[PDB]
Image (cartoon, rainbow, N blue to C red; front, top):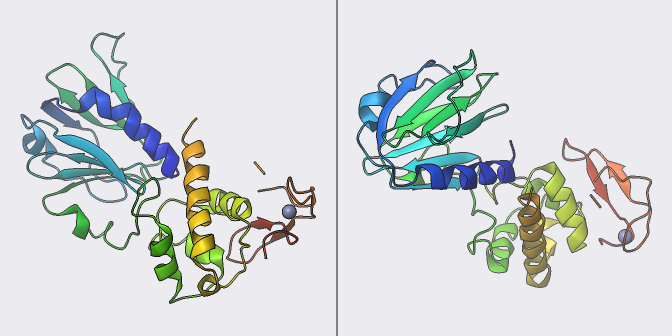
Length: 252
Ligand SMILES: [Zn+2]
C-alpha cells in the first residue's frame, strides 16, 4: 500500500468508527512485524475514539489516553462490518485483530503476510520513533515552495533521491516522483540546490496534483515512446537504485 491507498482506507474507515465506543478487542495474533500489546482489550474497552487521521503510511486512531497506530505494510487491509448489513463472516487464518464496538460495528484487520503493525502509544505523535524523522505531508499547506527551497539548499543529490526521501516529504514513491518531475519539467538529474523558488513552487503543486488524482480511485514505463508535450524520445535510466523516465528535451 502506497500513500493514496492508506488515505482512501482512512476516508473509508473514519465515518464508521469516529465517535463510537470500543466494547471489546479480540486478538487472534500478537506478533506481526512488531509485537502487539497483549492487553489491548482492557486498554481500549469503554473509551470512545476521539478522532482518526493519517501520517505517511500510518493510520492513527486518537483516543483520550493515547493513539493506536496501524501499518498495513505490504498486504494489510481493514474492513468494517455494520450490524445493519449482512452477516459477519467467520474469521480467517489471516484475520488477526477484531475491534468490536457497542454500536455493533466491527473493524477487522487482515494481513495474510503478517507484515503490518498494531502499536499503542501513550504520548506525543510528534516524537514517535516511526514518525519523527518524517517531512511534511503532501496535501498539506506545510508543503510550500519556501520549505522545499530551504530543504534543497543543503544537499544536492539528484532531484529524485530527495523527492523519494521520506524525511524531505512523505509518500511520493517511484511512480509519483517520475510523473511529477516530468509534469513540472525539472529533470531527475538536476542538482537539488540549483533549482529556485519559481520551480519549487510548481513542483510542489504538480506533486500535490499527481497525488490528489492518485487518490481519486500514465504519461512512467513510456521509454522509447514520444513525449506528450515535446514529443521527445524519453529515456529510461536506473540511477537512484530505481527506474527513471524523463524527456531529455524538456526537463533541463
Ligand atoms: Zn518532452
